[PDB]
Each structure stands twice: as structure tokens, then as C-alpha cells.
Image (cartoon, rainbow over all chains, first blue to last red; front, side):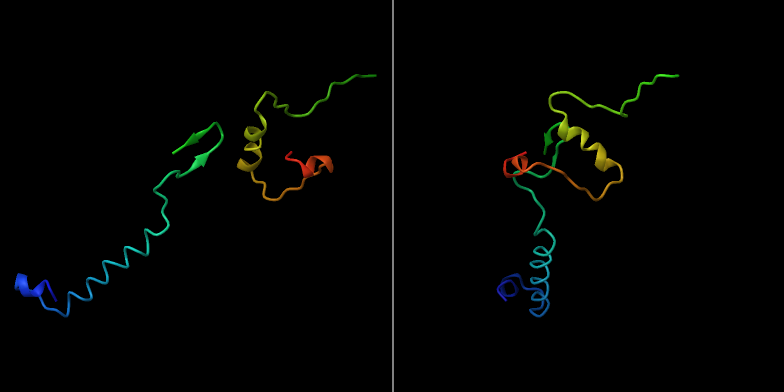
Length: 49
Length: 46
């Protein structure tokens, strides 16, 4: 409701079911994907990633 | 009469050889296992 009064376009009823779709799809797939510290470990000869 | 010379199929040996050979018995199809051990070699870390 605060981006419609300044910008001058858009309807208020459609910017509400688009702000909720780009904030829970991005907390349903990148929840458990390790990107810190250690990723994997194969120990046939010794390597880490 | 006739003599012979029989042996196993394979003898892996050198310092640092246990975790690497055991990879060979899971790259082939083997799912279930069983172990035998003394009582002194179970309460410790062997």
C-alpha cells in the first residue's frame, strides 16, 4: 500500500499475492543445502571440499 | 605321489591398509555383515 501512492501505478490487490510467493518459495527449497564449512568427504586417499 | 602349494587369493599388506581395502568389499555387491571379536577387543576402541 506504500508503493502505490508514490509510484502511481499498480493495483493494491495483486501486489499482496506476489509478495507472499517470493518469500516462502525461497524458504522451502534452500532450507537444507549445506554452504558453510564442510560439504563432502571421501576417504579413499583423503580429500575435502 | 604329488605335492602342492595352495594359498589364498589375495594378501593386502602395508602400514595404512585397512580402510582402503574394505572399500573393495562395498564396491561389489555386499549388504549385510557379521563380526567376531574377543571381549577385550570390544570394551576398548578396536
